[PDB]
Length: 153
Ligand SMILES: [Ca+2]
Image (cartoon, rainbow, N blue to C red; front, side, top):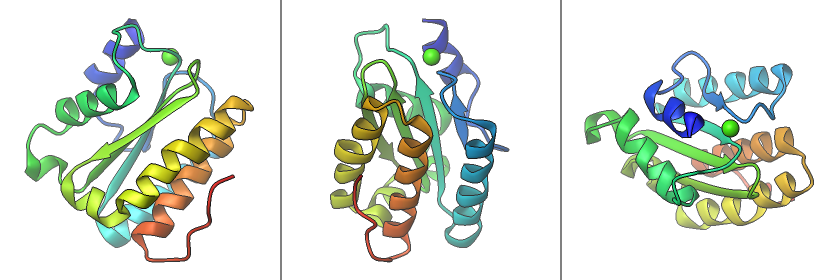
């Protein structure tokens, strides 16, 4: 699809932290995500990007596309080690998270798994996409910072 291509082609969103290809997030929430994630990058040198896409036409699921994106945007470990990518497919209510080793170690599998099985699908199913993405960001940031887990919705 044009969406799947554009997301891969355009490269990582350096000034914004979010590629909202599905058009489901507001200007306010994208600004709030920029505030939260540019602060995480400043403090911890981890860059977390979020991508929304309405549906995947290649028969790839969300994790396969997230990994494809990580490898295309950051083609070496020097470039990808500290990077994380969260993908939300809005028609399917499915999310996935991947990233370089330093990012994955910082979050931990428990919170990676919890965010994709709780915040993302539950909130998107109720069409609360801004909350889905912002609550998932806050939860991943809390894990990276060793703060108490805010939990799922
Ligand atoms: Ca889309």
